[PDB]
Length: 56
Length: 56
Image (cartoon, rainbow over all chains, first blue to last red; front, side):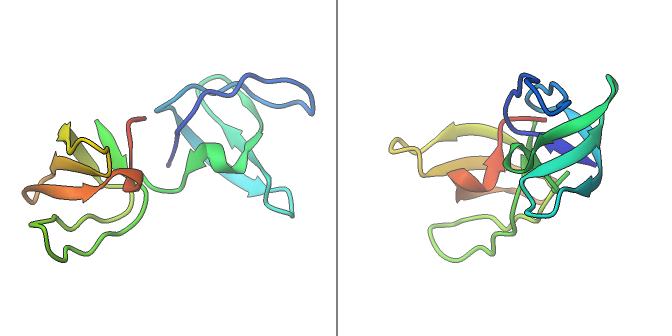
């Protein structure tokens, strides 16, 4: 699993909204490593790389 | 709860060892905010502030 460290409000680039301490599962990156495609109990989308942690 | 983002090997200052993705409970800080006094399934001690996350 992965957990959210900060809140992210979805803007453009079909992003996803995420709240702190949230459980998400990472499916892959974007190349330069700046965005992750994730799934939560709410859906699937791009979230910033430094907002989540591979720990947990 | 709190979760560990990186591994910390206990040195001096009666620190505690912690592994990534670990669950710990914070009891208080040290003042300048650089160290946290925590408890895990292994014990209790000082760990660096930026090594853990209040999320989870």
